[PDB]
Image (cartoon, rainbow over all chains, first blue to last red; front, top):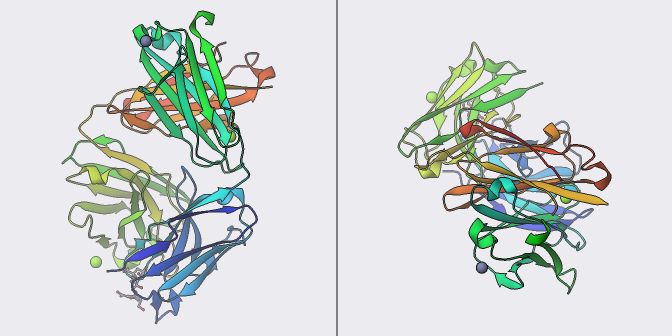
Length: 219
Length: 215
Ligand SMILES: C=CCO[C@]1(C(=O)O)C[C@@H](O)[C@@H](O)[C@@H]([C@H](O)CO[C@H]2C=C(C(=O)O)O[C@H]([C@H](O)CO)C2)O1
Ligand SMILES: [Mg+2]
Ligand SMILES: [Mg+2]
Ligand SMILES: [Zn+2]
């Protein structure tokens, strides 16, 4: 059959530096009749469809920045990005079309940047939710780097770990940061037994956690 | 301008069938092979099959993973491509893309649709609850889109006019329902003096919601 394999699985590179990734086929993709390698590269940015970058191994599609260059032949191919930019964050796929078509497993390119502290915001349950018997408290931790972050919820000063939804965005295409949402969900009955609700974020950018709180009596 | 637009994705039970369509314009349809490709959430692209162009008698080929179970066809009068899926299973849950393929010369998929999401599951359709997130130089506001099934939902802010400084958090499945949230950050001088509204849609339940963020 034709097995396509890519390397690395993932990597991070700083803006302005060079990126090299590789694509192997289990069989030569060089068509002896047309003298071309039937190997294309696609870029898939977060939440988008794949976009064609390179085909016949080295032909750069119209409108693709000159920083993207495909090379190689036979069973081994390379995509090189010189002077990488924040917007190049994406999964890159190679694809053979020598015998039907088969995609490689992708290489995830992340962007390294300077550490950045999160901006933290807390939100109490809406009256339209409380009326239904539930109470979700939301904390946004926005625009930080690197991705690793700790959030604790404290209720009247005591840590709680049950009832929590955490979700990270993909890296931002403009500023190369991450954001995270943390949602604590309680019943209205339990919500009404306590006053102080606190989101505490600990990130490598400070030894001091960022603390956001609200008090039910103040709503 | 070349346009490819998939439709027909949604929730379907295990063992069921579903047919996707892909409307096209902006190129000579019969000149081109057309492919289908799918992507399970967070996983790699998988080529499924193609239908050849008129020069090659519009014949079909399929990956071993779906041969005998999926069928590709095309309407050459209206320039629509179809994928019939049968005996669906959980492993078929994925975003499905149509892509323009070979023209007898170039080896490339020039163009891809936006994709249509298929979910194979026994769970029922549940519309979201949509809750405003208002605070108790910049101000951050949000919407909580809670307890829906299946994916996806769409969230915009002020009908898409606020796009900068928006973060929409990927949905998370807990106890058989999805929840997501979306934040927007705007100058404090502009809210609440100017209106901020999240617009949420859940196509599975035809839900359309506009939630004004009120101080
Ligand atoms: C024209 C048919 C071949 O094209 C495809 C196919 O399977 O339809 C699709 C294309 O993207 C390539 O994968 C080729 C593959 O390179 C084989 O190409 C051939 C084989 C044939 C054939 O008739 O089966 O004919 C081609 C030329 O037209 C003959 O000069 C070369 O497969
Ligand atoms: Mg941001
Ligand atoms: Mg045939
Ligand atoms: Zn309690």
